[PDB]
Length: 125
Length: 126
Image 1: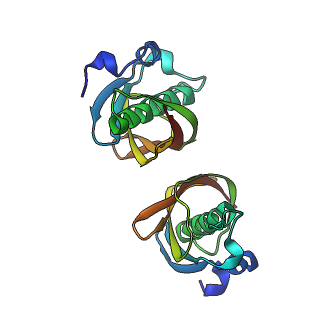
Image 2 (image 1 turned 30 degrees about the vertical axis):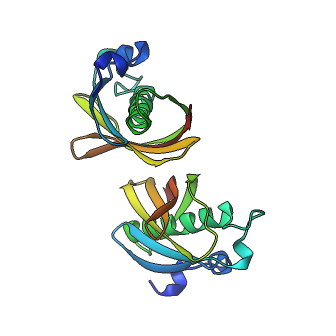
């Protein structure tokens, strides 16, 4: 697909930066910015989740094809480390691609450090 | 591995869970199919698969903090990928983070090259 079929208005707002995708894997970068700060001055959990959801969505698209659609049914995330500056990278991998649903996992890292880990389910449209 | 008696409970025995190995923040447990594990569809019940996962995750935590310390499950989330009708399954759990107060752990259940279930949970360090 073109860059266009992989971004949305919200992904652009948060500052998500897709890096690569293919065979049920995707990687997306997110630089820290002032508007991502929570009350403690670190990257907001919502921003981290947003990053993960988008990366998972792109991984799914790479599995079933961009000529087909899937949507998030549910997702679960754990927050492991705070992010105060710099950038993070999220990598998502499709673990199962069924006729009706896909299971996807993802991790967010800063350098080698684990920042967040998640797992979710997508509905195949 | 410590003695088997140190790694099992009445409930793990009931289900038929069988510790296989322990590493540094990693554990493997096996579960053979049996009549009393069947759900209404005649396959391994989701509860039995979850029980396997929870036990394996606990053992992975113990291999991280030591069996001289304790942790308990705060929460867990599991996805069921496909049904198991016979034979046995293996669960491997891996500690992803060991903090002073909590641990995050992931686990997968397989039968060979078949992914059966996948999950992620949080333990409280006691």
